[PDB]
Amino acid sequence: LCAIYITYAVIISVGILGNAILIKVFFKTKSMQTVPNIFITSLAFGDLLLLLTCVPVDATHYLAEGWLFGRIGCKVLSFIRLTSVGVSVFTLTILSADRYKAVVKPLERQPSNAILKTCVKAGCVWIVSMIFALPEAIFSNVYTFRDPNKNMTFESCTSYPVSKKLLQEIHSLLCFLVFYIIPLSIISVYYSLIARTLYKSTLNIPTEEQSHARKQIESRKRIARTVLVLVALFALCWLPNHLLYLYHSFTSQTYVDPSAMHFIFTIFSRVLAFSNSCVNPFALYWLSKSFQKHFKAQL
Amino acid sequence: ELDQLRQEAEQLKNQIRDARKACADATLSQITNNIDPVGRIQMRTRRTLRGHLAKIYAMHWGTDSRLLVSASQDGKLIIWDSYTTNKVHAIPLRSSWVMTCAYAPSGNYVACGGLDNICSIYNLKTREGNVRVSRELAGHTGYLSCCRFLDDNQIVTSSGDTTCALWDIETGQQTTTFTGHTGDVMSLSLAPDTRLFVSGACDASAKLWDVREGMCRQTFTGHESDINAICFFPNGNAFATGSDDATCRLFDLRADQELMTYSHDNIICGITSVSFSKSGRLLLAGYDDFNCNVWDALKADRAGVLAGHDNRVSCLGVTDDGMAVATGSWDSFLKIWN
Amino acid sequence: TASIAQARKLVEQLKMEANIDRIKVSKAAADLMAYCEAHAKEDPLLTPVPASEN
Amino acid sequence: XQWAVXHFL
Amino acid sequence: LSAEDKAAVERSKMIEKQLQKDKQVYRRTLRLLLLGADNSGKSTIVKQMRITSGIFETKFQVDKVNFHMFDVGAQRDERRKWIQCFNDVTAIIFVVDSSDYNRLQEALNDFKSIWNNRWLRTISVILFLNKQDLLAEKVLAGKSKIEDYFPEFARYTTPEDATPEPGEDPRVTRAKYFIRKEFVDISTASGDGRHICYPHFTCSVDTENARRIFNDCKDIILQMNLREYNLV
């Protein structure tokens, strides 16, 4: 309607399509159901939920006068969205750790076909996400805010009541420290170590081999650059929304809303906050070669 | 002199071919066209073994269909319980590259072999409780491909040196030898009567040897590639062979020729193991296509397909009582079908 | 020495293989079909059986 | 507004 | 669940614990195959690595990881059957005598046959061109010319990107690089990338030999991991 909803809809559609094809490949193509791949598909699920929980959340924030799903509606929606975001971040950092352990320490490969271990790890990650989301779920609620420009009230979600603004702030900070600082730092260090190891391997592997080793060298350099750009995209996508939420929590302006140009900014952040969800599948699509083959096959 | 012997050999070959073609009045197919069809045999996996570590290469059933010895390429012989799926004994082999294993008819001893050229006969009923090397016989100039027990004192072993050998476990020496193959012997199946046994080698032919007499009674040259698997027919009068050509051939000892060739265009992968059922109608054969095929011994049509595994099926065997079929593949997992 | 030895060995092998009693393929096929028809009543999978016995 | 002034994601 | 079933379950659990420990100890070790004609100095290579038996196992340790090298140089020449068991292994060290130009063609044929093998199509081959000192002495003496056995050597120029070691005569360097490029091209043919060859120059007194195998195995395992994790 405002020339921006179309871009958000297209992003959500492409992300849903990517994640759906990814899960369909993981299920149908059993050959790709190895030990680590579980984690990968887990992320997709999270992403799916996020996307499946992103359509309504925004659909009610824009092109609407006030909240629609009600009190329990906002409760469950915020709970599931925060759980999906936490699961996504945790699975991303776990995949980074696994790639680090496999590339930097290739001789320490764990036992294969141990699907039970990865399943228990994913279950623990999901449980930790749900536990860390329970606070906002129990404290979230729909409240009315006044608008002096309109001289009327409008209902909207709030992770905490206005009477405990400070509390909210603290939570927000914690969320940041738990969703941006430590995850970004660990992913960055792991990807840097992986890229350094890949470069040292490309330098160590025989380069004189006639058109047989240079191909692997180029592939290793390409995947190293991809891994290095992954963390950059993750940061550029999760910094805008984090700063937006920090501003909203530190301000917590009640009975008044600054309806300035800020609108575009926040929604822009949202788009970026979702771009990463679409980058994770395609990222993998860029890593391997036969992966693209069976992806286009199932697609 | 050499020319005379060459001419005599050629004349004998021609005479054998003529005598074999003369008796071919009718093929097994023409006579088996009037019998009712076997139909589709949809088998299902009842048990799944998850204990093996490396590629499961060899397995064999004992007198009882409960115990099942299975050999892995990590140097491990596991005695599974087909009923409860429990593990009975675990024998760490001194040689990791094991390619054969057998369960004695008395259920007390188990043998094996491989690239080490030494056959290790173990005892399971030791009073000490743990498994111990009862005997370690050597003498073969090649790798051991298949082993089978004739009794609690004698054991036949086929080696890659193109010759088989029947050993006395008590004496620990070659009770007798069997030479004549021009290629490495890959499989050996004992007849139900225990009097004779057929063996196939890399050469496009198989030979039927006698236990009491150290000589071959019949030789079959109806092959195109290396015969990898061989199984005696339950009646002991015929036997099925399977080579890399992906075509199972049923040779009858009484007719001394191929009766029915089980082949298909879409099947190109070689054969690794073959087995028969209690009745013999269902002829099972493992292929390199990550699955097994069960054909009709009479109709020759494909009766069923077992595609549960995800890697080359390296061994397969039906129980003596006819209740299930074990299949070990390189995926380190053994599946029991019924 | 060795060449003539193996030649004579192969000649004797082919001789003892040719002087073997043979029969028509029809009788062997009939005997095999009779064995199959007689043992079908105890075949593992040719005939269905209840899970109580399995 | 509900685009306005709170809540993560 | 009678007492006999209790004892059976206890025995099964004990055997499962033992098998898990054995699986850990096994996956902690790296298996390797060793191949080479009788003329090759594979025996000397085995004797240097001090860091009717148809199979010969040698266990050693490098960089705190264990390597078990298995040699089958005590069996028939035909190897289209027993070589299948050595699939899925870390690497196959192929030893060739680069000094003997006569047996060089047979070594090339054997390497081509092993590389194009169906079951070993996804396994790398560590090519150790042993006996480099003898090759250097021979090519310097000038008594035996490679052109007599390989006409392409006369029209083969030294690679521009080569890295001649200090003190190496131009003829020796060119000869060794040509012999290496021979195997490199034999391996590149029919190779889609699933497996590659690792050529290296060794001698009968070369001490820095186990490190080459260590690096080759580390690279192979890293590439296999990248393949498994869908990273490449």
Image (cartoon, coloured by chain):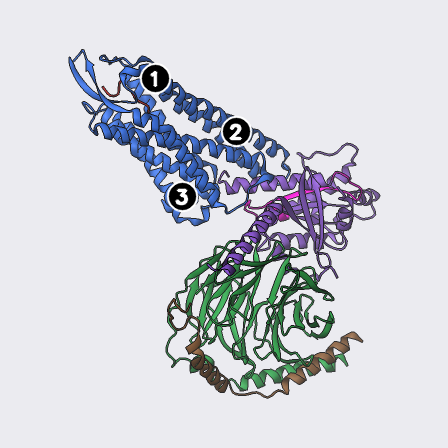
Taking the image as shown, residue A103 lies to the left or right of residue A15, namely right
Which chain does red denote in the image?
Answer: D
Q: Which stretch is magenta? A: E185-208
- Measure the C-alpha gap from mark 1 to mark 3: 46 Å
Determine whether, in the image, residue E86 is placed left or right of residue C40. right
Residue E188 colored in magenta in the image: yes
Q: Which-is-in-front pick, marks 3 and 2?
A: 2
Of A125 and A30, nearer the camera is: A125
Instruction: State the image coordinates of residue A142 (x, y, percent, origin top left).
Output: 23, 23
Residue A206 appearing in the image: yes
Residue ID for mark 3: A295
Q: Is residue B172 above or below residue E62?
A: below
Q: Amino acid at mark 1?
A: Leu
**Res C22 → quadrant:** bottom right
Q: Chain of mark 3?
A: A
Q: Which residue is mark 1?
A: A167
Question: What residue is pinned by disc 2?
Answer: A190
Quadrant of residue B161 in the image?
A: bottom right
**Chain B colour as displayed:** green
Instruction: Determine whether the residue tagged by mark 2 lies in a helix, strand or loop.
Output: helix
Question: What residue is shown at x 70% (from left), y 81% (from top)?
Answer: C11
Q: Is residue E56 left or right of residue E86?
A: right
Label 1 vs 3, first from the N-terminus: 1
In 3D space, how far apart are the residues under numbered discs 1 and 2 (Cα atoms)?
Answer: 34 Å
| Count of numbered badges drawn on the protein | 3
A208 is within the stretch colored magenta: no
Work out whether disc 1 and disc 2 sit on a shared chain.
yes
Q: Position of residue E55 (x, y in %)?
A: 70, 56
N-terminal of the two: label 3 or label 2? 2
- Quick check: do tags 1 and 3 share a chain? yes
